[PDB]
Length: 531
Ligand code: NI
Image (cartoon, helix red, strand yellow):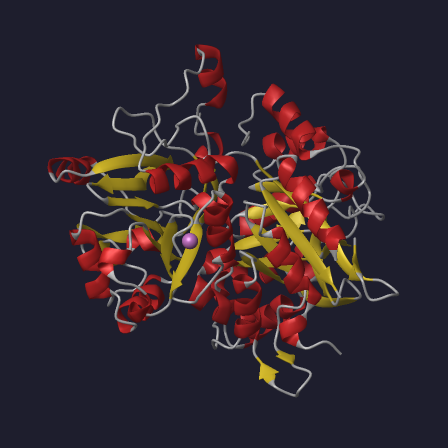
């Protein structure tokens, strides 16, 4: 209560708040959750944080309905420190095209707009950097990386930058593709970040620390050599080559969780060895509230400060007491437990099939539509399990096919990828081309592209499959299945338009660490997060 400095965090009770509070306590502070305006008073609050995720209107409505507008404004007028995160920062603007009818606190008189997806994938999911400038603040370092996950942003141009300057605002800029946007803002006692510091490893913790301590450390004296190596060259739109570490979560004979301190320690190890993200593949008469996978996330979230994804089990379920819990709420539970993204599998295929059946339209009942409308496309990833099928010509199937470089058994020069469901035990008559385009239309923000035929092989990724999917959709595509050695990552990043690469057994077996891969990619002129 007064034995350590207390930090007040406004909680609209939606999304992952585990990481932020764990980050604050890790820094030696006591967290005080404010769910109601009654939970805090101006004079007794010295450090306030406004975190937010998901749909703009969804967040701001929740915020002002609970009665936080006046309290927030009064706190700001007192001159005391406030920090906004993600939607917390966008809540400072006039509003957002994302939610046409929503109004913001309007400290910055323009609205957030969506990134241009004709030249790059949207949402932006990855590690971007702050453009070098004389007016940076709170230790933001151009040579370090921060994690961004959003579709909308305060996109800048010459006029807006000048107006902000004359307005007395200090801006930390970033660029994704050809678009320049606001990475962070600072004016008097207001500080806000578009990226998630609690998801940005050590670099992120530093930013939270500098804010809590009200300090703007000078950036390290990097050698011209180090700068040229750590600087953003705007390859891959300005995002580093994202390396994901994946692990399975099973229930053994005795009922314990295995690959509950095993899945937890391995995720910690992955994190410590440089993983940019940790994905848990959940393959498990237990009540939803007591699902052991949820404890794994919660425990992992105490020290792993990078995004966490969980696949498997995120669907409509009937609890032990017969309660009907829809996908959306099951997801909310994993999110509040430490998860940042949820991977949909089998349902994705059903949803896509229905989509085409309805004449290429969604009816809003799929887990993809519900979770994404609440948390944003960035919170939903589609796990696809496809396998190559050869045909003599586009005429042998209704699905989209492409001319392959590797002829089939009978000399077939064309093929399509047939999707499966239920852990790849059952195939459907839907190509990966159609599955991904439908899911994207339904609101998915990213594709986790597995490949049955390469899975477990350790001989590299199916390169034509990656290109086939990149031709189909505009959302980020993750290369999965086949990774064995660092060179496989190099090949995907240089020979294909893959937006990220996932590795499983190679990291689990200790053959290579994420750092080994990063060191190798780094040695080959690729940009990678190093923290
Ligand atoms: Ni105390």
